Image (cartoon, rainbow, N blue to C red; front, side):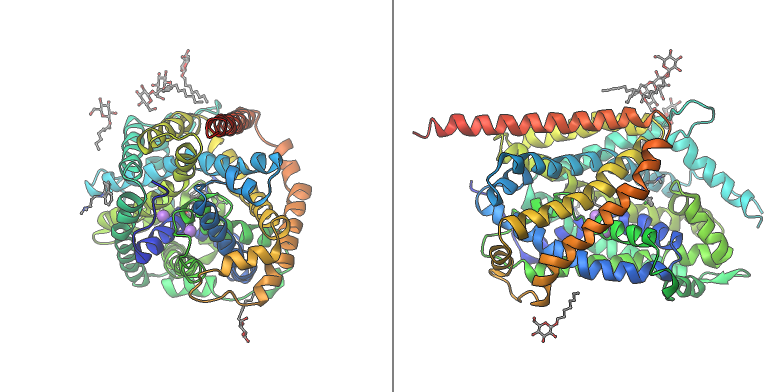
Length: 512
Ligand SMILES: CN(C)CCCN1c2ccccc2CCc2ccc(Cl)cc21
Ligand SMILES: CN(C)CCCN1c2ccccc2CCc2ccc(Cl)cc21
Ligand SMILES: CCCCCCCCO[C@@H]1O[C@H](CO)[C@@H](O)[C@H](O)[C@H]1O
Ligand SMILES: CCCCCCCCO[C@@H]1O[C@H](CO)[C@@H](O)[C@H](O)[C@H]1O
Ligand SMILES: CCCCCCCCO[C@@H]1O[C@H](CO)[C@@H](O)[C@H](O)[C@H]1O
Ligand SMILES: CCCCCCCCO[C@@H]1O[C@H](CO)[C@@H](O)[C@H](O)[C@H]1O
Ligand SMILES: CCCCCCCCO[C@@H]1O[C@H](CO)[C@@H](O)[C@H](O)[C@H]1O
Ligand SMILES: CC(C)C[C@H](N)C(=O)O
Ligand code: NA
Ligand code: NA
């Protein structure tokens, strides 16, 4: 062919919206917000969306469409197209490494939601007794802990239940069944089914939650806590780092995923309005839907102070333990739990296929593998690698940090510098607006060229100076097992880019 292309504009928008709308909206956002003072988190969040989220979204859509027009959907080649320096290809490897590493733990978490959905649907759930908080949360904590196999001793090892393992296998098979059908007949087709389902399930859950009321509060108290400003924290670096990190994660920015999806957009197609729409749809799903489910429910039943303590407790407690526990105290609560996990599963699935496609696109575009082989090998690498996340306690956290937290911010800055500084601000601006149904507001030219990069640069330095040291000095030794492995993955991916180069050289000397 030349390239596969999104069939319809609606399919394109829903596929991109599904790329973005995932576990980050319903699980990550609530914890981050509650953990950072709720309303106090929102100001930096909104600012990050305007100064970082929106501008980078347009930039990645532009880079992808630009690359696609020349038959390239991933950063190793696209970065090179924008800056013909071998170093561009190496920096580009992060556009394959980040999504791959994130997929290695993201699909596993996604599989938990399918496993929970299954168990809640058939009623194989814990039975709490008769209004102490712990006698109520404990059965659900044990339920999660037995599912993933949390360490009961001193060894930093996890023991996933057999059901969890088999469900991960099924989950991988489901991701493959969609990806193996390609862009239009696979990802786009699925998005047209999943997004509407996702929206309906989420609205229903918000409505149900809004009816919650106990001696400790109502869902309204939850919304008040999340949407009430606290200008006295606008000066804490930590809240800003959390806010910006969430924006990157929730919009799928810096993962090379938006770029790859955009590489299937026809060269002439608009990306300004489409990009803004995908981004806007994600924010609504995040702040309106995701923000209105778990926090209001937790606050209604336990009050703000306890809700916050829950979010800070961590380990998927809010979404996999607390919410289902709360639901169990209501009529039809087990089924509500099913709907919650089913919602999470579809949110995750539409996002995981998005972070596996970069590796698939690279194998197809640069190594010329058939889609079938590219999808199967990608799945094999993710499946194999995930065993590290399934059996080594904290490996998931380590990957989520280096690739999904630090990595994306670093890559976002990198792609911006390459596209807006090296490739050329005016050429980049031109490329972004080309074919647009609407033009990017002019003030954004200055935001992209000066504000965004300066913003990310400062964030990254603050990170390396007052946070990375603790992570490098105060963690259990087992973190090095994961660091070693993912560094190895980077090395391997660089080797593949080298092979792509050599294949390119040999076909050019065969093109003459
Ligand atoms: C009414 N049916 C069209 C929906 C079931 C098909 N579907 C689907 C839809 C569009 C494009 C690819 C795929 C692949 C198979 C698959 C796998 C899992 C799920 Cl959760 C849905 C699903
Ligand atoms: C601290 N870890 C136990 C958890 C890290 C995983 N993670 C994550 C990663 C992918 C998808 C959903 C979620 C939900 C939980 C959550 C909450 C806050 C943060 Cl900042 C990360 C985070
Ligand atoms: C292909 C790479 C394989 C690495 C070793 C994988 C071992 C998986 O082993 C399986 O794990 C499940 C969940 O913990 C258990 O329920 C099964 O009984 C066990 O056989
Ligand atoms: C979606 C269907 C998943 C079926 C796998 C369920 C695994 C849950 O549990 C396992 O089931 C096995 C066979 O029933 C038993 O031999 C194991 O002892 C038991 O732990
Ligand atoms: C870095 C990833 C390494 C994965 C190696 C997994 C080896 C699996 O090991 C197996 O796990 C089962 C369930 O936990 C146990 O029941 C078996 O006794 C054990 O041998
Ligand atoms: C990241 C690696 C996680 C590994 C989890 C391993 C759980 C293994 O289980 C252990 O395997 C050993 C060797 O087979 C046996 O000698 C032990 O008796 C057994 O408990
Ligand atoms: C920090 C980023 C803020 C983005 C808000 C942009 C609001 C758009 O602002 C509008 O842009 C148009 C096109 O440039 C101008 O013609 C209008 O006069 C201006 O009000
Ligand atoms: C890594 C990304 C695909 C994650 C997705 N944007 C989410 O919010 O879950
Ligand atoms: Na999102
Ligand atoms: Na999604």
